[PDB]
Amino acid sequence: PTEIKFSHVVAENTPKGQMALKFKQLVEERLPGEYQVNVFPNSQLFGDNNELSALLLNDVQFVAPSLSKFERYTKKLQLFDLPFLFKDMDAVNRFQQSDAGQQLLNSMKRKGVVGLGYLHNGMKQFSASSPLVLPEDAQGKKFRIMASDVLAAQFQAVEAIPVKKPFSEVFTLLQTRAIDGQENTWSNIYSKKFYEVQSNITESNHGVLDYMVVTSNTFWKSLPADKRKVIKASLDEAIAYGNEIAAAKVNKDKQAIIDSKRSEVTYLTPEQRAAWVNAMKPVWAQFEDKIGKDLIDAAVASNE
Image 1 (cartoon, helix red, strand yellow):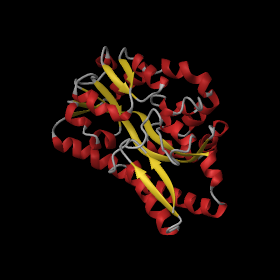
Image 2 (cartoon, one colour):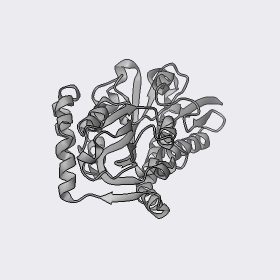
Image 3 (cartoon, helix red, strand yellow):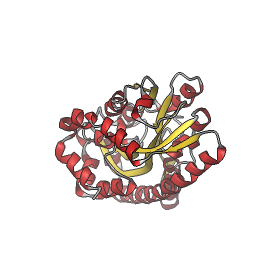
Image 4 (cartoon, helix red, strand yellow):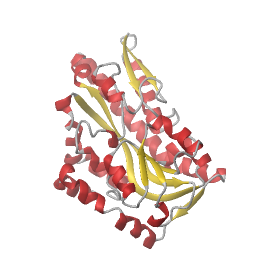
């Protein structure tokens, strides 16, 4: 069988981990002996910094980076990093499924990247080794971020110190106290055991962590049209499965973290949330011209 590689950076028992395995299952059921999908979780094949290059060089055929990790290829996907842009995952999905959202799947074609679909994880929560209740609480604290200029600006807006590091490095940076805090979904916090070395988590819902599943023009064009259709169908179904898992993990992994008693979860009052919102609004102005105001207006409208 022709080998198709799918690489990613998360644990297996996560939305993206399960999406990738379901994709393998379906392709191999439908094209037995013709295509084999080998899945490489946990940055075993490629990590954050080199996966898109690998994709375009055809050393891997599918990857699904966070929407945050595409600045080299487009300035538009930075949209998804804007703090407090989407109220919740229902708004995210409405935006992604709309014409404005769907067009972004093609935003990188001129550099070789083909967008195949969105895949959910969830809303991001702040964590640290100390409480994060008001923006002032973040002052002077070092936070790991995904490699995103918008996320750097988010933390600079509250006088914190952002450091861009690949996902594979976060556990050790927290364990050694080389960083104070981070931001992520309950699924990543739980599956990577970040909560074991973060005494405090705030249910801030301050941004979205979702993915775009992508391939290269080279690989996608190389497939016969009939096989491409079967592979695309399998991917789409695997995405639906992954999204179901993402929605379940939000509740289940939050609960598991609380049950562990390792981390105190703080819930914000309306006045506290408003303070964070107000603090993180220089950020939108800084990036609106590059992202596109009309595109931001579309995303804002998904909250209605």
